[PDB]
Image: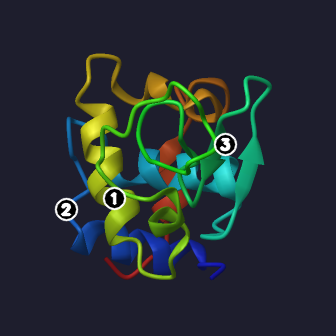
Amino acid sequence: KVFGRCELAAAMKRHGLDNYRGYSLGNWVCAAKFESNFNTQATNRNTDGSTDYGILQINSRWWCNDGRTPGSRNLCNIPCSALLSSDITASVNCAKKIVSDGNGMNAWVAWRNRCKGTDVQAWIRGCRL
């Protein structure tokens, strides 16, 4: 599913992501924009053989099982395919774990490089929230 901007903002809010670990909703929408372009089916293979999945490009090295990342962990206790669903619940639940692990949203390289320090409220501006 390719979410619209304000549509994703609403789903993330419903699922408790807004202000989670101190990160306002615009931070999460901006991260999804640059990780996946709002596409729940996004995948990207990393140099090490791990893969990033879904709207927040969650990595099989640590967080999900894809059966093809020898030596990896599955800290979210989920198949990586769960992170591709039209329903964002699994991606939100796992993103809450990741952002809690010490490094905040710096876990998402596109957020650090493209959202951090910017006017992230722009991503939710005009939405009916």
Quadrant for residue 3, please give it.
bottom right
Say which residue appears at 66% left-offset and 79% top-offset: 2
Q: How is the image coloured?
A: rainbow
| Secondary structure found at label 3 | strand
Q: Residues within 10 Å of mark 3 (few under 14, many from 20)?
A: many
**Mark 2 or mark 1, earlier in chain:** 2
Looking at the rendered structure, which numbered label has been put on residue 16?
Answer: 2
Q: Is residue 123 left or right of residue 95?
A: right
**Mark 2 or mark 3, earlier in chain:** 2
Residue bearing mark 3: 51
* Three-letter code for the amino acid on which mark 3 is drawn: Thr
* Three-letter code for the amino acid on which mark 1 is drawn: Val
| Secondary structure found at label 1 | helix
**Mark 3 or mark 1, earlier in chain:** 3
Are the residues at dot 3 and dot 1 in contact (C-beta closer than 8 Å)?
A: no
Nearest the camera: 52 or 112? Answer: 52
Q: Residues within 10 Å of mark 2 (few under 14, many from 20)?
A: some
Are the residues at dot 2 and dot 1 in contact (C-beta closer than 8 Å)?
A: yes
Looking at the rendered structure, which numbered label has been put on residue 92?
Answer: 1
Q: Is residue 2 left or right of residue 21?
A: right
Quadrant for residue 103, please give it.
top left
Q: Nearer the viewer, mark 2 or mark 1?
A: 1
